[PDB]
Image (cartoon, rainbow over all chains, first blue to last red):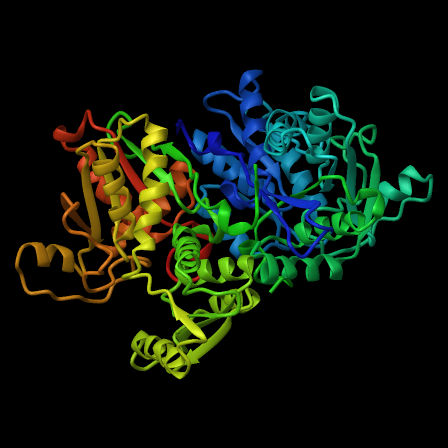
Length: 310
Length: 310
């Protein structure tokens, strides 16, 4: 029916079958670009704010502070705007000027730090701002805030189960904060009782989950797959539900993304191309030929036009 | 469940209540930016192609030719890509270079005409290309192709009826091709038996529907409300279901659009700001205080960032 504000309109994203990936239709994609803010992060921007209200840490008057690497800050921005919260978001001068303006036009009180050290400064500034008056601010902390995976367990997971009628066999998701694969896996494995195969995807340039699980020295490193590869293990990544970890390089993630536009008519971001390249690999293994593979496409295309993707 | 391709995933867009427009919640918006291609036009790109198949004019091998003023060409582009059709789209050198590239990355064989005369050349080229071999091409003709309003009568209309439980009293829609208000109005007035108020919206700069219905000389003229104000009466505009015509100027359409971002957390285009300004006007008339007003928001924000809107 009718949503009280734009925060409630999250989710119910479509599953679509791919024709030029997989084997006789075993790869189906879940299009999270089909959301407010054009990415999966709307789901956690909404729920981290709802939960902060449920527990009283968010009150009719307090101000949201956070630092953001991109999609999340827009999510929180639109939810704050929808629900009428002051929001401060911190980000260095290493930022897109189209990303600055979007945030600003969202009523974000944007904090511009120095580029140099990277995101460690703006994040430090984000705790710094809170440190001034903790009673005035609340930092939502997507990497460790459990409301992040709990929304995927409550929505994104059941949506997958429902739309496939319980027939999903594998789920393929890149990991940034890890909340996606976590919430979904728990949903399907624990609430819906089905021992699916949960596949984490990361960049071959910064393969810290793979290096970790194999006891190998952890060596994070630069990459272009925007949205994943945080370069450490996030607290919202539960390695206990991860069955398999696939790595994908940036160039293949791009080529796959472009390929989805030109052949599938699906316009998604570099991270969505990374996830499909991972799922395609598995789908074309005789052990997965009969199984139903569900791949999360984290974001939509038109918010990557001016980096590499175009 | 699972869509065979991205064309089938159109529609089921949300209704959201506005908090800073209308009077005690009588204005609710339908967010058509929440679609593949990020606009309502995905609905006609999909259906004009489906219907052309139903009637045999589109065959496994023919090529789509059309000229486009923007959103429609992306819609057709993604549907052609999804359904595996060659598409030629014509457009002058008066085009966004980010709009060119999106189309190109969609596998569009783009035709670049001369700017000078405007869109009359690229359209003429679009018939010109067909004129070479009509057996090779098919021109879908959104302004007069009835599959355009029939999709809104089949989907967008019933979605409104269903989500409001039949309680919608007024529908507010800007008119470009007119298919939106047409299909929706017929749906609700004729199929669902309810004598709602259908309100067309146009720019005060090019008020040809208003000048027409009042017998006044028709004087189209330049405007910035992208998506509406075609500067003539389209064949897919049935003035027989239009109860009222509101005009809105470009500056107010912008301000209203920005206002939806900053206060509602709804990121939409200039034409969506035009439609809400029209609906807000009516909503604050004592005669509409009790009635439920539904406003179509035709497109999403991130595809206007680089003109005026930002």
